């Protein structure tokens, strides 16, 4: 009778369907690069 | 969900588009040169 309780649980393991968003790391990378420009931009203004 | 808040911020870093006006220093230079004539001009008049 427990087999059916597991049927959902087999499903539950299954359904997760948005896990590995790697290039999350790559909008993170864009954030890190543009926001790496944020670090320097008033120093343009400072040299000048 | 924060990625979009950053999308503007990536932009915001970007948009600044009139920063390095170097030859500002060179109308400054013209000011400094002509206004360097201002310093002496009544001394023409004084020698004479």
Image: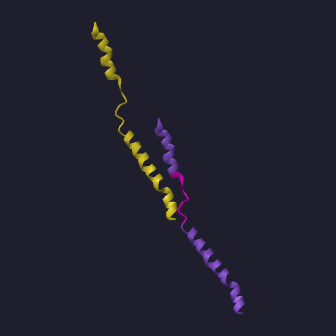
Chain colours: A yellow, B purple
Vertical relation: B30 (above or below) A10: below
Extreme residue in the top direction: A1
Q: Which residues are magenta?
A: B14-21
Quadrant that contains the N terminus of chain A: top left
Q: Quadrant of residue A20?
A: top left
Vertical relation: B21 (above or below) B29: above
Q: Is residue B17 magenta?
A: yes
Q: Is residue A19 magenta?
A: no
Q: x, y percentage for residue A14?
A: 32, 22
Vertical relation: A20 (above or below) A26: above
Q: Is residue A29 left or right of residue B48?
A: left
Vertical relation: A22 (above or below) B22: above
Q: Is residue B48 left or right of residue A29?
A: right
Which residue is found at the position 31% from the left and 12% from the top?
A: A5
The residue closer to the viewer here, A31 or A23, is A31
Which residue is found at the position 41% from the left and 47% from the top?
A: A32
């Amino acid at each position: 009778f427990t087999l059916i309780e597991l049927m959902i649980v087999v499903a539950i393991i299954g359904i997760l369907a948005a896990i590995a968003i790697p290039q999350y790391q790559n909008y993170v990378a864009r954030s890190e690069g543009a926001s790496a420009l944020a670090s320097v931009n008033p120093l343009k203004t400072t040299v000048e």
